[PDB]
Image (cartoon, coloured by chain):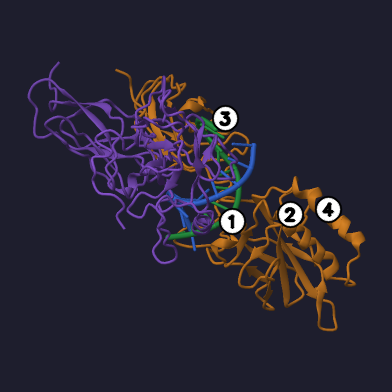
Chain colours: A orange, B purple, C blue, D green
Amino acid sequence: GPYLVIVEQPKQRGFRFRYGCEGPSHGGLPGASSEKGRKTYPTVKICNYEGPAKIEVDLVTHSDPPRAHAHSLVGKQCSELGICAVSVGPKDMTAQFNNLGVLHVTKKNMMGTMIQKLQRQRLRSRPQGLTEAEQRELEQEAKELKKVMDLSIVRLRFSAFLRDSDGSFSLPLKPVISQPIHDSKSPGASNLKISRMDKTAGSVRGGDEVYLLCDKVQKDDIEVRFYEDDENGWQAFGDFSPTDVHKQYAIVFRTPPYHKMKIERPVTVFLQLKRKRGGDVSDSKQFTYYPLV
Amino acid sequence: SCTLGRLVSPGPCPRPYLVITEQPKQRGMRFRYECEGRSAGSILGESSTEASKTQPAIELRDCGGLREVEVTACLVWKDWPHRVHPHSLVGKDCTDGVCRVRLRPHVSPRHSFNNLGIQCVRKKEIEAAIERKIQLGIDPYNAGSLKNHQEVDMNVVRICFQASYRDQQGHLHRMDPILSEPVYDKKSTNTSELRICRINKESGPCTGGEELYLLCDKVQKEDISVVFSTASWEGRADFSQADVHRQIAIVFKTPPYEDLEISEPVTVNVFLQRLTDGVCSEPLPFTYLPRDHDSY
DNA sequence: CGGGAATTCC
DNA sequence: CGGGAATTCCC
């Protein structure tokens, strides 16, 4: 029956929110399993359908309780400031949103915005002429949310709707939400990737310097890690000393002593940057080892 | 027109004028906006020191016969039309991009400025900011040419000096303006001061081709080149903008020596040279090795 | 569909 | 204020 399912999920981290002074066409929110060679977009679907139908989709507040948001989703097929709605053929009951971007509203404006956006959810619909009464509440619910809506992480809310006879859509459905998406810019949200590193070949024990180049990272919430656990884990860091974090985009440290008791042939392990709180990561960088001499 | 002739009336004696004794440190001072709310800077003197850092000091010459004189520090461009620069100079006794000090001529003719700083106005103001000052009659050379050819160096400025004298009589003449050795903002990547902060190894075979890493301060990839200059030789590495990791790191390849292997190794200095103006940086210690070392 | 300059804020 | 970093804009 009223069942909906997000087939492909939106890339969680990597899409750069764009400011209005930047333009409406810098791209469309990609998908998790979307890479070069073959792109992929935030597709949803409907099982046990009832024929042709639409799918309103707006940006909600990351806070689990699905609520609005100041960042108005923008794109070709978008209600100017708000929801982007598409349709589906009788058979193809799955919607895919290629061109889909997000408008980043400034901190100094996420105020007058959200409030105004609220006025519409009120004054706009239902009887017109909103009374000074609501006005007060509007101003409340607005500011009474400013400090509980991460201006850098949003979730899509795919809300499907059918036609309730008389030839008119209005029959709601089960609006499901897409796992959060971190603004590719917000200091604490991008993807902890790693451009490249200095000396590739390590050593053996635990104490070797190597110049590592990376992407913007904060003075903490950062720490290098290497491993290869076909077992029940195994880790090792490098240097939690900030002094070595060169202007956000670089870190130099000393190789940790792997419990490589077996000083036999050379063993190559995995290496990848991680975030403390967020617990991000990077790709498989090859860090080989060698027999001391 | 001409009042008097070259009568030996003055005679190699009068004719007062001023002079910068200590220029304001070229580049290193972070201009600030009226957004960062500030009033006092820290500008130093061209040749200061992390220790007893000197300061912008100037004196007067031929101030004899004078009772009290007033100085007029103000910001103007850096080329021919030294128009009144939009950035206003803030600090003590600075009203509108201008500072004044009723320094007693005779009894110690010299003023060392302390809390002194600049204020950089956003670009979408620049012009109007020049109009405002204009209106308030501010232009040590009256040459305001707006709307046509602009391009104002929002990173550098010259602080003009207009020193007005005063005698008992009603003959308050004015000396001639003095310009400063251009000041460059530290916050600008293009004109900041260059500085390496670390490097891979200190020794590399003269065979070259060796790849070395390096950290630095924000530099412009599309305009910078690391060198291995020295007495008798000057060979600069090679790499591409692609190896300029986010303005704070370089991955270059040590160029071979000037064809040499003669016995034991010879040390050389390495530093950065901006492919635009030349400004070099504090050189770092590096060493070349005489080819291989086949032995026990 | 990224890089980094220009501004603000802590 | 210094010194750094987050934020908004402009190529």
The residue mark sitting in front, 4 or 3, is 4
Instruction: Assess whether mark 4 and mark 2 are in contact (beta carbons under 8 angstroms).
Output: no
- In this image, A49 relative to A36: left or right? right
Q: Chain of mark 3?
A: A
Label 1 Cα crowd, 10 Å radius (few <14 / some 14-19 / many 20+): many
**Depth check, front residue: A272 or B93:** B93
Q: Determine the secondary structure under disc 3.
A: loop
The residue mark sitting in front, 2 or 4, is 2
Q: Determine the secondary structure under disc 2.
A: helix
In the rendered image, which quarter contains the C terminus of chain A?
A: top left
The residue mark sitting in front, 2 or 3, is 2
Q: Which residue is mark 4?
A: A141
In the rendered image, which quarter contains the N terminus of chain A?
A: bottom right
Label 3 Cα crowd, 10 Å radius (few <14 / some 14-19 / many 20+): few
Q: Residue at x 68, y 75 (%)?
A: A87
* Residue B14 visible: yes
Disc 3 marks a residue whose amino acid type is: Asn
Tag on residue A111? 2
Between discs 4 and 1, the one toward the N terminus: 1
Q: Position of residue B120 (x, y in %)?
A: 50, 47
Q: Position of residue A268 (x, y in %)?
A: 39, 32
**Depth check, front residue: A30 or B73:** B73
The residue mark sitting in front, 4 or 1, is 4
Q: Residue at x 52, y 50 (%)?
A: B121
Q: Residue at x 66, y 63 (%)?
A: A73
The residue mark sitting in front, 3 or 1, is 1
Q: Which residue is mark 1?
A: A17
Between discs 1 and 2, the one toward the N terminus: 1
Q: Are marks 1 and 2 on the same chain?
A: yes
Q: Chain of mark 4?
A: A
